[PDB]
Each structure stands twice: as structure tokens, then as C-alpha cells.
Length: 163
Ligand SMILES: CC(C)(COP(=O)(O)OP(=O)(O)OC[C@H]1O[C@@H](n2cnc3c(N)ncnc32)[C@H](O)[C@@H]1O)[C@@H](O)C(=O)NCCC(=O)NCCS
Ligand SMILES: [Cl-]
Ligand SMILES: [Mg+2]
Image 1 (cartoon, rainbow, N blue to C red):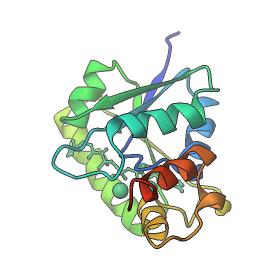
Image 2: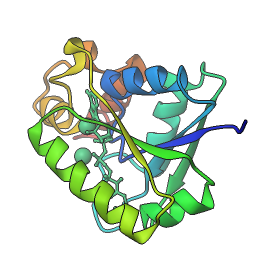
Image 3: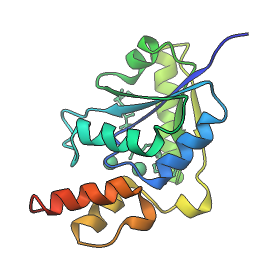
């Protein structure tokens, strides 16, 4: 037969309950799921790689078939390196759908073995993005409903260093 491996790439800055839903769902359909955190040298995350991985491990580590790894560079090279079956993305909105369709096609031209599968969020996570969460935290709003508890605490230990 064979054994399947999907990469879920993102900045996860921070992880949200949305991402958690998607990884859980994906872990039911594939043998190995790789949560791949883009380091993002030229992109300026709020949380470091180390915080980002830690918060991820903290929310999804209870799934036996999920790994966590930082990467930079070209997704397709990461894809080959990781001997992956497919990439997983979530599609929240029309712009997501437009972007990811283009990207899939581009990656298939860079690597004929490339593959993208997509999941749609349940309605209770449809409105959640990392960006929105950062903005709400920044303005001292309460993000508890939308993110795992560790992430709440992480926001505080930044508001506590000052932010
Ligand atoms: C796509 C990049 C920028 C990272 O993505 P992003 O910044 O969206 O990460 P984020 O963690 O916010 O989202 C993760 C993924 O799950 C989806 N998602 C986010 N929130 C939710 C939610 N609540 N419900 C469902 N899905 C969601 C997103 O749409 C996204 O596809 C990254 O893959 C990348 O750029 N890789 C390398 C660069 C590259 O090779 N570029 C050019 C050729 S590809
Ligand atoms: Cl982002
Ligand atoms: Mg997001």
C-alpha cells in the first residue's frame, strides 16, 4: 500500500482554535501530520519560533501522529525534503480560495509530485484568524474563546514584559 504524510504550513503567530480543529481533523485522515512553522526571517512575527513551536506542542502534542518543525525557504523544497504526500491548507474565504488555487498550480509546476488538499472550517471557527487575534490582544481585548489557554498566558507574559 504506502504511508501518508501531510504538511500543514503556517506562521501560527499564534496558533488558534481554528488551526487546532484543522490539525485534529487532518490527523483522522492521514497517517502523519507535520505542523510546519515558517520561521519568517523577512516577515517579523510577534512570537518567536520557540514560543510558536511551544504553544503548538502544548495544544496538539496529545495527538500521537503530529510532528512540529520550523522551516524557511521554498515550501516545495520542504515538501521534497519531508517526503510528503500533500500540503494541507484551510480555506476561510474567497480570497483564500483564489490565492491557494494559484499557489497550488505554481507549486505543481515547480514540482510535478506536489499536491494541495483543502479543508473548510466548521462554522464556530470561520471568523478566527491569527491576525485578528493579535489585533484584539494588542487592544487589551479578551481572546480566550478563540485560542488555547497557553496562548492566553503567552499574551499576558508579553503585556507583562510591557506590550
Ligand atoms: C502560506 C504561508 C505564507 C504561511 O501561511 P499563513 O501566514 O496563512 O499562516 P496562518 O497560520 O495564519 O494560517 C495557516 C493555514 O490554515 C488556515 N486557517 C487559519 N485560520 C483558520 C481557521 N480559523 N479555520 C480554518 N482554517 C484556518 C489559513 O488560511 C492557512 O492556510 C507559508 O506557507 C509560506 O509562505 N511558505 C513559504 C514561501 C513560499 O514558498 N512562497 C512562494 C512559493 S509557495
Ligand atoms: Cl499572519
Ligand atoms: Mg490564520
